[PDB]
Image: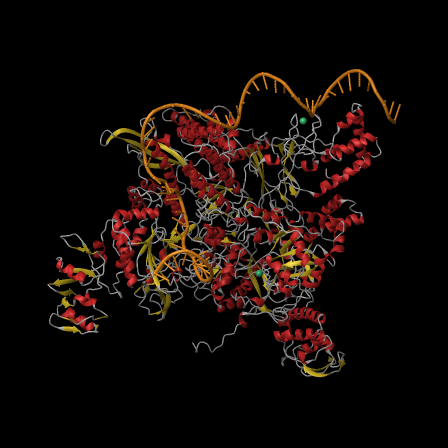
Amino acid sequence: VPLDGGRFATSDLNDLYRRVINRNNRLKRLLDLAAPDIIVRNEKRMLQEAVDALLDNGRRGRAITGSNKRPLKSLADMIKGKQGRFRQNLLGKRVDYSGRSVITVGPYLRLHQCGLPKKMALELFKPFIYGKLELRGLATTIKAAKKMVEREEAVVWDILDEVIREHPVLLNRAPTLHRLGIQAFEPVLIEGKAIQLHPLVCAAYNADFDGDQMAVHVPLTLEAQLEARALMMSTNNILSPANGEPIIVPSQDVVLGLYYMTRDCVNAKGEGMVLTGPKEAERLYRSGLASLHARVKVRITEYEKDANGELVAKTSLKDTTVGRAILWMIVPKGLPYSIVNQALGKKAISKMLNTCYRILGLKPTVIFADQIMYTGFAYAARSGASVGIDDMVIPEKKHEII
Amino acid sequence: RSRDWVPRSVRRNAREVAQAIGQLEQELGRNATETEVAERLGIDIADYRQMLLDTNNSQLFSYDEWREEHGDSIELVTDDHQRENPLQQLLDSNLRQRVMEAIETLPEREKLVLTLYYQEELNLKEIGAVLEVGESRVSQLHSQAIKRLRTKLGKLL
Amino acid sequence: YSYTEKKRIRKDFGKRPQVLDVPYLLSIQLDSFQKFIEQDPEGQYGLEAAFRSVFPIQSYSGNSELQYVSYRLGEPVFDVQECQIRGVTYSAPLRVKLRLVIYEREAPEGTVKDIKEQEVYMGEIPLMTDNGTFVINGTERVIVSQLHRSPGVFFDSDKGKTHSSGKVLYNARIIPYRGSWLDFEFDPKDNLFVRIDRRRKLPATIILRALNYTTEQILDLFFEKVIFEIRDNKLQMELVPERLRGETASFDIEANGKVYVEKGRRITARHIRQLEKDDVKLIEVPVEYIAGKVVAKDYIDESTGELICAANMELSLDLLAKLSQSGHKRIETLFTNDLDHGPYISETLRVDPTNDRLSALVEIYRMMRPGEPPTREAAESLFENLFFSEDRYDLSAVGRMKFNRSLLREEIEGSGILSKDDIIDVMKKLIDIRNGKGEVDDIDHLGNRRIRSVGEMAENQFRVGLVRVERAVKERLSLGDLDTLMPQDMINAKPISAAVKEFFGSSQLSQFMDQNNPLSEITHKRRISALGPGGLTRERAGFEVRDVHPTHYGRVCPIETPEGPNIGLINSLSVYAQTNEYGFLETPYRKVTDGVVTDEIHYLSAIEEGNYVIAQANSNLDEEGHFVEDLVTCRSKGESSLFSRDQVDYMDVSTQQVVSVGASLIPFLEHDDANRALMGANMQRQAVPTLRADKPLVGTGMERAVAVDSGVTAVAKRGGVVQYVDASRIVIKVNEDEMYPGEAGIDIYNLTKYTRSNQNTCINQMPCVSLGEPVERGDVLADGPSTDLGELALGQNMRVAFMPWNGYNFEDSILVSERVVQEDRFTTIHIQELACVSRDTKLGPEEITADIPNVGEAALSKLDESGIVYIGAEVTGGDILVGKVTPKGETQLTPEEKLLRAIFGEKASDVKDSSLRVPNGVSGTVIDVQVFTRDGVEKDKRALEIEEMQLKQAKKDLSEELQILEAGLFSRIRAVLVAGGVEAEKLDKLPRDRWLELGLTDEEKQNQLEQLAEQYDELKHEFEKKLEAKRRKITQGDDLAPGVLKIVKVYLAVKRRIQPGDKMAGRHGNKGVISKINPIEDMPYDENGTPVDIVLNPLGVPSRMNIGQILETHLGMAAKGIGDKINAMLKQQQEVAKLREFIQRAYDLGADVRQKVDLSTFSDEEVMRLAENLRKGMPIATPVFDGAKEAEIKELLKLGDLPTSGQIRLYDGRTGEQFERPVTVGYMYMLKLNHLVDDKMHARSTGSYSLVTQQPLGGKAQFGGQRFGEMEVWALEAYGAAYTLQEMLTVKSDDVNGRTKMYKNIVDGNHQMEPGMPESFNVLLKEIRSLGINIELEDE
Amino acid sequence: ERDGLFCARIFGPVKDYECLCGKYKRLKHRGVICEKCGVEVTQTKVRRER
DNA sequence: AGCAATAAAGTTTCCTTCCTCCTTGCCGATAACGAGATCAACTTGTTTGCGGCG
Ligand SMILES: [Mg+2]
Ligand SMILES: [Zn+2]
């Protein structure tokens, strides 16, 4: 095919066909004369050499090149290595109805939600829009849809909101190690050009928020839509098939909030007084009368289903820190009160959740987890939390040892 | 000569500019004052001005890697002008049935004239031979069909 | 200090007395090309070296000959700026001296036959800037300096190659600078072999005969003669006592009359002492000791001529008898202490088939030249060529030198060609280490690696072109006429220029430069590799080179090299690193003499150091005594340890010499992890300058030197006073003493305003100077893009306090206010360039014209009559720039478009448009246009307007110039008429030209009127001359590719502001994404109402250990207060003496910082301006390891009247209550980067495709679809959702029918599917059958 | 070009298809009678992929 | 309003047609120079098979 300035670009295959043909034609011309045999011999040496070099250049004899000193690429490497159809073209695919961007965080979100900047998603559900603008009769035909769309009317955004509800999508970090490297989320449109991301699935993706990128794909049809809503959704993908553990570890922050608050000092104040329930711990501390971290006696109402899966209510009193009181506010009606009577190391939360799932079923665990995130972020912000050069500690018993 | 596929007098002129330009570059001792080329090879400017196109531009290959290690080839940085497009044929067929829609109220032969010439890509004056009226009535009626289709709206202009 | 320094001083806390100020930094490229071009007479380098290397040429006969004499260059036609503008390489002429001399071949050497001594132009060449670059075709570029292995010799030993053995195999290698390598080797069976350019193995000894050597002489050289002697029946034999050493007695070893070693008995060291002692060599021995011994030399019967035993043949007792009676009472044999003296050569020989020399040459030829007939002289010529022809072999006596050292000779130099002695000696050294003596050595030791520079590359490509010449030159000498053939008639200059152009345009070394920030360039030219030709490869090369070697110390920075697969390979030069003259390295060191550090220096090698000891600078020195402490950590032998004080030889200079400059500049390196220090300085180059140039406050000391030596800025060439000033240019008047006489001495400087970078950025300059003010030499006069007052400015300093906030700083994510968005003070610009060309078709010419059919006038409104935009406009995607059009042929349409044209009826011309337009997604401002058009063609009219206003400009500039100059000269032209009378104001009032006739006296002064008119004529003539030259050069048309008619080119301007996603970080690896911007009102704030700027996540301090960022932060808060304390006073307008004392004491804080300044020196106005600059904050230098201290941070902070830890009470903007704890707060100086949200984002529904396979492309530039890998398949299969994949592979990839009908169904509301088969499948089938195969398929 | 690699002749197998004045040729429009001269024509067959 | 006439104007065909150009094949005029190499590759590397290779 030709180029901008009339120049050409070609396939070397042709070049190899040519030599073959020349030689064969020569050979006929020669044969018509019954010539001495030696030139015939040479003619066929050069023949077969041309032939197999067509098939596969530098295998038998050393390779033919152009002027560049580079091979005249044969067939076989249409099929071979990575370059071949298999590993390049046939198994691995370039794709339309796809996109990507840099990402970031949505903390407040719910797990199933994912941030969408306007214009890309706008582009992506284009033919749906066109169908519905012929539906409403705004765009009686296609060009009117196009033209109002490139005019970006408010109705455009209204119908965008109309469509994208319940309209899930597919998410991809690179590289795909295990099957959770991708997941199936539900959109929430946002005003930017960068995605927000629910924090906890940094680990399924090995993601850190320092400048990575993700891509997005689409179950255009319904079957795949429903599969992703039913299989790859954030709710199914909560335990490794490798070893049966929660992959929902709250790594580093919310842990801190919980450990800090759910803790037993002695020093502050109000040590050893009496309440009805946790709502009074809220009542005081939101007025700021008590140390949350202070063992004090209160009354709690714990529930149980020692019956054949039927609740068994009771209540009793506890010398406990205030935060434990508060955090009982959120436990969903199945647990003992021993669950909280320590200052909550990481694995305590692991087993918190494990128990929560294996007893109570699934969805309460999810909900429980969500509020753990929200509240621990909240009181982490409340916490007051920083470090200094003075928080570095040097034992006086170092220099003498050395 | 067999392998090369460019003409001969071409290469004569190429040899000639080679000899001449070297000869005169040593006459002078510096370069690129093409008016001298117009002089010494005093035929015309446009002649060589074309010739430089003709000669000084050779072919290249397709799969040369793209430079700063093998990011991609030249086979991925290519473009086309003769592409497919789905809606132009769509609306063309729409306009085809609009043509019959427009002309179905108009005289019987011209209906069939413009149908069978425009539909199945057949003969026009084949019909002018059938009637044998001189194709003047054809002319005004064709004008009228245009006046009839200039009663509606369509973009793709 | 200097004026520029009086403007703004940066404090320091360094304490060690510095000896050295850093040198000129990029001396090396300058030097290399300088020596390359320069006319060396004798001590040749490069070009003269190349000529005198290819010292003259003579004919295929030997009848005639050219001769070199000398050369010269020209000066360039075009200046720099026109070259970059015009679109050309910047180059120099070349001018050659030559003498065609001819010999009379009748006469013996009747040399007076013919002389044609003339000169010759041949080729231009490119030259360098004062900066380092070569522009090419209007493209500024740089080539890289290389590292690789020396030539010479090299020893090594593989360890268990046939691992069944688990045995060592030694071998030796020789690598000429140019010519063939050579390899000597052992085998599992203790036998020597050789190969050239890894030819197949051969016995070595063959070649020894091939050099006309007999086995006799062979083992004479290699082997010492074990002499037996047959005294009338019995065997006696000579013995050296130290041959029987660790050896055991075969018989009754004794004397003539005395026993030393009994049977079975080891010849101890005692008996060696006896045998040396009592004076015995000749010892009776059994005849049986022979049988098994080998004859040394082919012994015969002299009467017969019969090899009773061929040489190198084991011996016996029947052969003893025959040999004894033959008249041989002495038999030389080989010594075999297989422990020490093994007869590896004897073994290698008796494996070798050949005896004669000639057949050995034949067999070598037959290997080397297989099939070809064995013609004698051909083999001789081949062999002489490979190593004994000056043509195809060389050493680069460095090779010779290193080799002689590896020979342990004395003579450094020699030839470029081998000798026999040398080869013999390498065989000897090989066998000696094989016995054990000595050792092989290493690669990573820099002493073995030599660097290589631009000059040499030029040399080699140049002489290559010379050889291309040599060919045809000889072809024509012998044949053509001699009398008439001018020397220049034969030649050509294409190939030379071709190579030169090539690697200046084709090499993997020559790259674009990184115009982003000064550091980027200066480092990128200080960047080292071992890749390209004569180098290595990523996948082949491994770990051993990537790692660290101790010799790197003080030459190479360990702390900048990337994360890519090329980790350890490239690494930047150290700071005070220098190069040996050869291409090795060196580094200065302070001598330690009598304990005293002598203040001298020596740039010591990568070898020398291993001998001596060097002291460390962190050592506290005892104040003109010596090193204070006893056990000083010194270093030698590739390691460090603790030594005494008197013991030392030398000391380093600094604490810095190891690092890079990219490394050196973050302060408090001394408190953090290494890897992330790498990351820090690696991104530190990758920044962008803001609109404005904000300083830092915490420094190291060096920023000024790079601020200078980048060369971006205005400079004080020569002292003066500011004459004229503007926002675009400057004029200076030069001081008298500096104003040397000939010129009037008025420098000027036209500045570079809004101009594009290769990374597409805003470039510009600006004054930081005033009018009517003196100037010292050297100082700058206007800033560059990213600096202030001669100091680096590439980021901004801002507030921060760190704590969680609601999950907007989850993993290092960042959160900020919004006031800075009002200030737009990180906002920047991205110039974008665009063009459109007119070309001549086969039919005819493309044209450019406003008029085009089927256009709404809306577009045209912004175009002029020719079809070109009005400058200053503001534009958007879809808009049109250039009304370009194309004369076209015709087409054979069909009724579809027939009828669409029947309907619309808008006529199709014989032309279409080829117009230039705004790409989708882009919008901005036009500010400049240029046009280029050929010599031959009418200049499209607006380009004439542009040439005319460019002439207007140039004329105006030169008018200004000469008007000023000549106005200085009008001073004389008035004053000297005053000499010779008085017309006190009858002079002045009447018009000034009409002064010549005024009162006129004879004797000398008629000549003075003539001198007047003379100068007048001179000057007007110069003016006309200058206009002529310049007006021609400007008016001169362009040089173009074939087919081109002319081109247009456009620039643009667009300005980018923050949106979240924007990457940013600081100087400690402290990366981060931005998620949200905060209104002020929810910001945490303070006692005094000040909210904060920036917020952070401190979980990643210890995990990362970027602790020095803390220290800064103390200081970040700290010195600010001083400025406020001053600005407080300022707005209060207190008093000078208050400023005086307060400032002096600011500088008078520390214990033992070196700098000591007074200000009673300085004037009041200096104080005012200084104070006025300091108001924003007091900046400081923290040297890296001679840094400040916590005492001192907290000292300044205690003066600043604040929490000592600087960690304090804050309340919430949202709710307005106090947090629990205090929080450390301060300022960081941080950055922005080029990984931007708009630079990266892309989506795609539907568009272009491939062609051979019809599936989509990739790349935002070409509307790219994303890729879907096998890994994503595997995961999906893990779930098991078939239909997804069906779709993913059919419709969104290949099935065209599929994509069509699904698009149809969707717009119809139908969300359903139908599959097909990929085209890409059957392609493979069609390949398969192509290969001669009945691939096929079984139908259902 | 014909007898070639992109051989026009295989798509236009010569001995073929010309009308008198030389409008329709080379397989391009199989079912074409060149109408001005009314000349009927036969025998042509198309691949592009074979 | 429907139907035709005369006159004019622009054609597409189209076909020759004779200038000029351009390209496909052939054959020729002194006598003898030298068997190529020519400017490259730097030796990844461990595992595994098979032909020797005793
Ligand atoms: Mg990451
Ligand atoms: Zn026809």
Task: Report whether residue C15 is seen.
Answer: yes
Q: Find residue A80 and report its horizontal and vertical position in percent.
A: 53, 52
Q: Where is residue C619, by image quadrant? A: bottom left
Query: In the depicted view, which residue is nearer to us: C1100 or C303?
Result: C303
Query: In the depicted view, which residue is nearer to us: C396 or A29?
Result: A29
Task: Report whether residue C1157 is seen.
Answer: no
Quadrant holding ligand 2? Answer: top right
Of the 4 image quadrants, the one containing the N terminus of chain A is top right
Model colouring = secondary structure
Q: Find residue A302 and report its horizontal and vertical position in percent.
A: 73, 80
Q: Find residue C441 and report its horizontal and vertical position in percent.
A: 34, 60
User: Left of C800 or right of it: where is C170?
Assistant: left
Q: Find residue C894 and report its horizontal and vertical position in percent.
A: 71, 34
User: Left of A99 or right of it: where is C217?
Assistant: left
Of the 4 image quadrants, the one containing the C terminus of chain A is bottom left
User: Left of C1223 or right of it: where is A117?
Assistant: right
Which residue is the extreme one toward the front? Answer: A34
- Above/below status of C952 relative to C1284: above
Query: In the depicted view, which residue is nearer to us: C719 or C53?
Result: C53
